[PDB]
Image (cartoon, coloured by chain):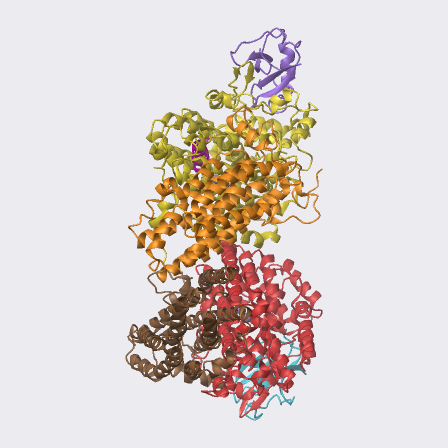
Chain colours: A red, B yellow, C orange, D brown, E purple, F cyan
Amino acid sequence: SMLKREDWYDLTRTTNWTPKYVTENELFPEEMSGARGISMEAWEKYDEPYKITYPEYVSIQREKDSGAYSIKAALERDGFVDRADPGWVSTMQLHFGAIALEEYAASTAEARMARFAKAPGNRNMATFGMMDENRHGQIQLYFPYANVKRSRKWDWAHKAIHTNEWAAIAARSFFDDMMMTRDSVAVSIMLTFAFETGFTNMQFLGLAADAAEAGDHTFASLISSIQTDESRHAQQGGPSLKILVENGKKDEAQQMVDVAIWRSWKLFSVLTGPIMDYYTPLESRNQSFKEFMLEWIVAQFERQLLDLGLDKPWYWDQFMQDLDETHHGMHLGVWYWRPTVWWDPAAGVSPEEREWLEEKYPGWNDTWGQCWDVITDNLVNGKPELTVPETLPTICNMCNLPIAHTPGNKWNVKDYQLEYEGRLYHFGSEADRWCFQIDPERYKNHTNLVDRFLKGEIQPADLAGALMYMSLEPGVMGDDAHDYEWVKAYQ
Amino acid sequence: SMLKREDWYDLTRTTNWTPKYVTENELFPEEMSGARGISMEAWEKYDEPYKITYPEYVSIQREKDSGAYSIKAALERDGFVDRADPGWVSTMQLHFGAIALEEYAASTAEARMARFAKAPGNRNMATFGMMDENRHGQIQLYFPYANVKRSRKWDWAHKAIHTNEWAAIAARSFFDDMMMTRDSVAVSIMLTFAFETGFTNMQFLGLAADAAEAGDHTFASLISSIQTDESRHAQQGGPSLKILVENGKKDEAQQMVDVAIWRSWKLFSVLTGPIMDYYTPLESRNQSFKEFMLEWIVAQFERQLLDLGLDKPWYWDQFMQDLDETHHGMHLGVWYWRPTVWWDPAAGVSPEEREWLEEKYPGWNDTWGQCWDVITDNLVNGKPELTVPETLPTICNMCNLPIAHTPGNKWNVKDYQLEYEGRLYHFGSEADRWCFQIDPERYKNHTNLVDRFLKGEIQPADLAGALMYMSLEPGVMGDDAHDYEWVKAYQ
Amino acid sequence: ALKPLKTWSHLAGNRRRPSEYEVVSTNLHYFTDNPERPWELDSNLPMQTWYKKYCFDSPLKHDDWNAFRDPDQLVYRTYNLLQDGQESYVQGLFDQLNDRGHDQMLTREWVETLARFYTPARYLFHALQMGSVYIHQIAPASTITNCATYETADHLRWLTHTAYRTRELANCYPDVGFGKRERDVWENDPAWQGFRELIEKALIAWDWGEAFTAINLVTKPAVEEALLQQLGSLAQSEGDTLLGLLAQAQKRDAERHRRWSSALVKMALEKEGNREVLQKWVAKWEPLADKAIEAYCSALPDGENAIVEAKSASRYVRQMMGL
Amino acid sequence: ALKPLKTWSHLAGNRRRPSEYEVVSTNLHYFTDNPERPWELDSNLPMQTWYKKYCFDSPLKHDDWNAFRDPDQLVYRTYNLLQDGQESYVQGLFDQLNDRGHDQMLTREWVETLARFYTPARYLFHALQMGSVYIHQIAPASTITNCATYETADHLRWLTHTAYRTRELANCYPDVGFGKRERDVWENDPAWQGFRELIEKALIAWDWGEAFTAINLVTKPAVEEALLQQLGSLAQSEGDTLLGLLAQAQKRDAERHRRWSSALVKMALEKEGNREVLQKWVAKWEPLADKAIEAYCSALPDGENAIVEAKSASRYVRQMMGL
Amino acid sequence: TFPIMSNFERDFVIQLVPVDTEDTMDQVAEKCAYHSINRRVHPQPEKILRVRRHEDGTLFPRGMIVSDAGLRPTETLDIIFMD
Amino acid sequence: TFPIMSNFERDFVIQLVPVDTEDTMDQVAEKCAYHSINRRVHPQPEKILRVRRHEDGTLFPRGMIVSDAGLRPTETLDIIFMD
Ligand SMILES: [Mn+2]
Ligand SMILES: [Mn+2]
Ligand SMILES: [Mn+2]
Ligand SMILES: [Mn+2]
């Protein structure tokens, strides 16, 4: 017979001991551990909500891949990707390039806790999380690999994060800040709690649904499977936060959550928002990006923050408001600067789509609809040349994204500048500038693409030069997803 | 370390022994064993071409189901079956009802060899084949089970073979003759060699392709997986035949092959031929039923028969010729008598389709096209009542299928009658009557649907009564697959 | 018009939603639809007669054999998951005990014991394989047949282990005759003649009920107690941990066969007269089982004690079924 | 316009089609793209400095660490298939040896031996888990990291076996303290202090090269020979076939770790000067390994002999690598 | 009642057709035409339908009755277009 | 050359716009309009474009030159429609 798991589980995490041949601080350096004065004994109260043992893991994860890889091989020669909507295809290329290697990097972020966490239970769970991200990085390379002969863009699934293309810089800015350069406790909070439990756990659920709605079962199976692993290791932040509040560190806990959530939000506003409000066909849009955020992200954050004795971030209302603008600014930026990304941005501003947008965002056409009016007329009158840039947009020195906002009638674009130690910084929001000020030593000498351009680090110092600097060439350089098909509807 | 399979395989089949407490004939009764005078030592030269051990089997078959069931669950809620072409849907309903329980019955046919075969190697391979058909019967019940709430017809996946609906009688006639009522050696020949290796091994390959072409990946995965098992146990007949020829039984071997092949052909002419020449959309037709037969079935039979020292059946040329008629007769019969089957027969005689048919079968419209002309005019002129029967067609007393052939200008319908012991029998071909005459004691007192009707065993003795006798009611009763949509093309 | 149901029509009438097991295993035999003519051919064919006499006219009766349910509820899909795990265990044992040279440290006395009492079982195990596969093709219901189907696979499984193991033994002790002498031992060693007579006679009991009784209720417990329990228990004592563990791993399949056999008997006892029918068959076969156990175990060390325990344990199997 | 390739652009230039292993495991670390500023933030952050000092400035050098290839070519998908099979074997052993009451027939002397020399290893195994997971996050190439990734999982695997096994032992011998006394034994028993000092010091060697050497080349062979080989060999002798087989099953993972470690060293020896760099680290750590082995094995029965064999076998690991 | 199998000219299938032992070949042919003409065979007013035993080919007189032609029940008959 | 960030009225994004230290607010505004007017902002011939420091709001004289307004490189300026 076998023992019941509950009868022996505790022993698997009864691994802390009192160092003697080296000191505790030597064994667990604060910069990597982040125990923050809390005793080892106190960190031992850490108790993971989702437990799992080695044997259960290898068995269950074996079947998950058996299924995912079996689905992929069964539909392989079906070549769905060839008849899929360009908005969808673009959605996948953006997804893989932006995330494949960050998934792999997350295994190191997990390894950080697995090694330096004073909480024994956190160390084992992080070992499994490490294994999960290893899977995620690998499976999200194996799948897109199937399309490399279709377009060079699929090569960015692997190449993207190795380039200085602006979106790649933005991604690395986020990820490195949240998980690669933080102590163990900080990672469990900013990454597993704030980003995974807070955003991706649900996003992936919605992504898997859209893939299914798009007819891409291979991709839907992929995302669903990955999501089940995330739902498991994302739990690590909860207990860390309780322990910090439970002691004398509620402020530190609060500050990390505030930073983490805002940064996750910014990245989210450029990578997900545009997709559901413009790339997914109108008939396949369940809800708007704003609705999705409220019904599946904001209510949960408040829920969670309450159970932990934490407060809503000071920027919560602004955040609530920004759900009506930000992602529209990000989409317009990406589309207008489409040759600077590796996927084909879908305009999504046809008559049918334009009213859907006014319906979901009253006041859209009065503001955003304006910029799009000009762009549309130019295309109708044979002036494409005016729908692509001849300069670089101002980049935020925190989220490394373009500083944009409400245009047209209700114009309200602003720049929260800041001069620090003889240099001028630009921020796309109050929160972005705050993130910097509360911890300037962490971002001080970093330079965004524009800073580098202004410093002469991009040569030749012109558009063509900026493109080579970002490793972009015709073939991968983005253009309108539906090849301006949506223009015919305007005479 | 582990041993190489080749080092110990022989021992797994070194199981024959000399009985002492009972006699060999008692242990291996001729009626079940069919050793036919060949010694046990001589049967021991049996050497399977495809070997497999228990451990390899359970491991490999575990993954086959992991994949098939994983595909099915991933596409389940996609509900492809709801948007699939009616010709396809009908193809599946016909397939399941006609084969699910015959697949299960085949495990007993395998069990017959596993127990009564004097060849040790045949006994083990039959044990695995028994397990294969157990899988086939079960998996082909589990899959259609998913659609029982869509239509009562899906219930026939389980019910069909329990009824006296004519197609069910035809199927049981074939299967019981070939595998349920034959000695072990006879089963290995007539079933695994003649039917599986000879017809189904390739058919399933083509079926899996069409499913893929139809967009039904769940079904394509199903058929592909099953096919791999068949490709394995279908090998059993080869060695049996060699041993019989190798000794003094080439005639007996020849006679079984001739019977088996013709009967397999007849069933095949009603269940598969119509499907690829009329149910599969025109744009998805790789080749014609006749082409498929020549390129994938007839050449192989000759190939095989040569390597074994056997001759082509005496009816080979007639068979070659019949590829231009038979299945067209079966299709017209099924369609005209559509309310007597459990699926919706597709007419497949629209302008576009009619020339495809003339293209693949020159002289079609001159003959078959005639009967269809009248049927079409009647429908155009509001006389549907003349496109459904008011009588029963003459049924063959061997294959239990309607006696039909070339109509119209080149009219050539014939009936190879035979009076035996005071009774008149009807046969749809020379070969059908021969099958009976070479072994009359095997079919003598059997009665087909018409015989039963004429004997007063169907009451009330009219159409409505025949329908209840066959367990058919509105809802499952067949009608035109595309609801006569193809009629609009005729004014 | 007929409206679609939620389950198969023959299961429409259940309080609870049918399980996969019921969906893929029930009411599948069609030869029972026409007791007067099981197969769709002439009613006088030899096979027509065989099923009428050995299936339909069996003294073990019931009005609805299709109601039988496998207590383990095995389906092909779950059978393989289950056995693939068990084979990973057994094959792992083979591989790693081989690695530490487990066979080389066996004594000469024990190796000879293996040659006489262990490797020849490949014949008895295949005989059970034949015995259970016949039950498969003559049983009155598809749920009963399936139990016989999986059991047959387990018997082939034991044969296979034995075959593999005989090869390994012949490699380290080529002069013993492993692989070559088993047949003559099975056919002429007085230690095996008890079992051989038993199974040879059992193999020609064509009545599905008597076959079930002779094979599953009488012969198997006798074989399992003698070859797996006793010889396995002795193997452990003599330093052969591989056989000791191998036998116990096979006992797991044997125990599952007992579970469905016990369920079938239980169902049979629902009808008046069946207990008596079963006891009469047991009373007929039991004497041969006793003889088989005595001839085998008596030749083993501490033989008399092996006989008492085997007889007792095998009889206990039927007692717990109410006989 | 750029034309699509047949493989990843960084693999376009191979004679043969890239394997799944190469497709999902190569050139994935991006922190090595900017040695002057590994992370996309201020170049003076503590983590920026940690990677420059412990990864980039390691004395173990090579111009293309991304060229490293795991000889076993493990990927997550194949790692799980592999280990799920091995766990079916180990878990099968637990289940069935428990069934035949394997623990109840252990002598009191051996049970106490298990309390002192066996169950406390949960601390040393988790320490290796920590040791290898650190190698994971500081190694210069993704193919090297992955090897450390899977190795970490194996270490957690050994911990797990030990945890489970400690529970079972505490059930049949509740007065020994199984489950409660391990920490104090690990921290105060002179038999363990050799290993404890070794791993505690090894755990703070931040240089990726020295970490690899101290953990994979020096500490592990010493732990594996002492705890798996010696104690396991003794277990077999004392009648504990479970531990004897369990240890051998873990040795399989240990052997795989040696295989990739040997490959990494081989690659390192391509560059002039690395052999000397490696020998200097080995020369620094070897003395602590010797001390660990002596303190552990000397306390075991026939202790002096266990010391000689462990020392010899562990040193052989590095000799076969050319040191 | 007397059953015969109708192999109507130009049709594709032979079918069961109940007739009377009193009917004449003409009336038999009329009962057969019902199941073929205008169903899947074009009429031919410019011709006459004849009844002949399918096996030996014998052609029966239009006014001859079923009972005189002998015939075995279920006997197959060809119904053909003539003059 | 001197770089400034252009936050053109009615547009949605602030952008990099190179100007000369000699240019006047008028000419600066003309260099900014190039990247906004007719690209994503409708012209307004019936109005004048003014240049004001985004941070404090200061409005600069149309004829005043970049070099006199002081300004920090990359300084953000609002280009607005007036009279
Ligand atoms: Mn992940
Ligand atoms: Mn994650
Ligand atoms: Mn099959
Ligand atoms: Mn088959």
**Looking at this view, is C236 or A221 the one in front?**
C236
Q: Residue at left 61%, top 25%?
A: B449
Please say whether residue A174 is visible from this viewpoint. no
**Looking at this view, is A447 or D152 the one in front?**
D152
Check the image and report above or below for C45 versus C19. above
Check the image and report above or below for D80 versus C121. below
Q: Is residue B184 magenta?
A: yes
Please report the bounds of the magenta region as a residue range.
Answer: B183-197
**Looking at this view, is B279 or B135 the one in front?**
B135
Check the image and report above or below for E26 versus A385. above
Name the spot of residue B330 as percent of width and height, x first.
Answer: 55, 29
Please say whether residue B184 is visible from this viewpoint. yes
Name the spot of residue B27 as percent of width and height, x first.
Answer: 44, 33
Query: In which image quadrant can residue B188 be found?
Result: top left
State the predominant SS element of the stretch in magenta: helix
Name the spot of residue A348 as percent of width and height, x first.
Answer: 61, 64
Check the image and report above or below for C274 versus A250. above
Query: In which image quadrant can residue B192 be found?
Result: top left
Name the spot of residue C167 as percent of width and height, x first.
Answer: 35, 50
Task: Check the picture and name the quadrant holding the C terminus of chain F.
Answer: bottom right
Answer left or right for D83 relative to B164.
left
Query: In which image quadrant can residue F82 be found?
Result: bottom right
**Looking at this view, is E15 or B466 the one in front?**
B466
